[PDB]
Image 1 (tube, rainbow over the protein chains, first blue to last red):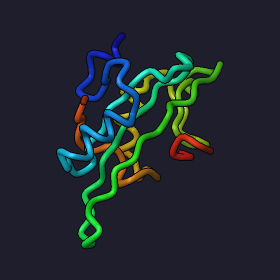
Image 2 (cartoon, chains in turn red, cyan; image 1 turned 90 degrees about the vertical axis):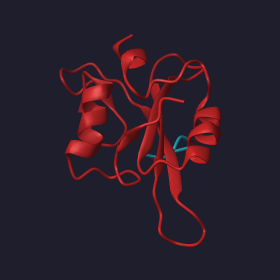
Image 3 (cartoon, rainbow over the protein chains, first blue to last red; image 1 turned 30 degrees about the vertical axis):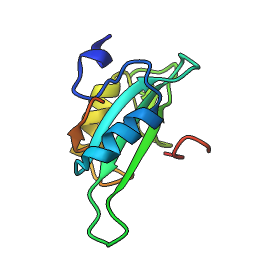
Length: 108
Length: 6
């Protein structure tokens, strides 16, 4: 499960735990990816470091899969790749559009 | 939509 081998794939622990556990850590761009009850797409739990007083902003995204290489997995309407990790890498290696993009792999 | 609408 290449995903489970990354520094962000959290077991069956829903993003709530990933978020709860991850958000508690407060890792700038801290992310993780777990398999949703609907074992079809991978859910990535990410935490963004916010300056505001309200505290940092952490968010998760369910990786959307497709039937076109590499546009297979995507957690955005254009970010589709045959590799969540790559896409994970893309979620940071490229401008991105989600909470300070993927930064730290806080695999729950 | 529910899951942090990427």
